[PDB]
Image 1 (cartoon, protein in one colour):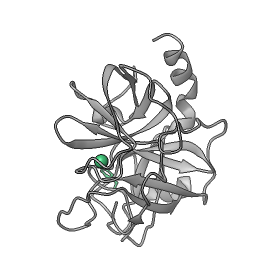
Image 2 (spheres, rainbow, N blue to C red):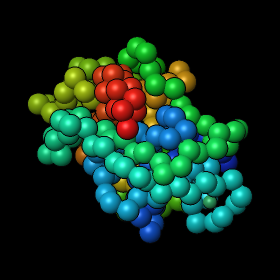
Image 3 (cartoon, protein in one colour):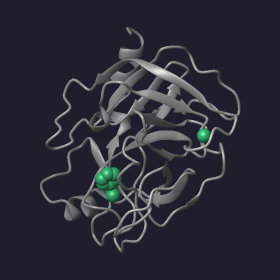
Length: 223
Ligand SMILES: NCc1ccccc1
Ligand SMILES: [Ca+2]
């Protein structure tokens, strides 16, 4: 997260870190047994880390649970990032309390102009590299469909939305990939792609979670 703020320990209790020997992507806990992340975050050997604030220090609220199954969306295209969503099943159910909790799936899609909360352990620099230890947050508005399409002509599908700031300075970044965009208490987006981080006229692009609720529900009912 570039241009954001320190969230506060365990204030984003649905945020997870995906770990393969090191943090590499975010995700969102949606059920005691399931995490939603980006399909571009797929890899074998994922450990899900719940209840994290500092990802480099054991602070006392963590649950580390190995993935038992990963399910990349059937129509994921890694070239365009269309359908950039994946479900991860946990080997055992997370224990739910204040510091670890699920986030609700949306009923309706989110509105242009709504201020959402984006969070993660990704790079904090637009130019150069610095990776934080504690969870960072950014309040960012959903941009209009026409603005989003102007920023990425020919590339925005109905399964994507932009959020952020055209002036630059405030954005998600590498390492935030797969993490949540929460609007009005619902998971509306997944950190997906863009062009760099916090550059002028290149806002973040997010998987539009409302289009996937039927697939998520059916998949969790059968796996
Ligand atoms: N600045 C949007 C973004 C986030 C994660 C990865 C690539 C691009
Ligand atoms: Ca920790």
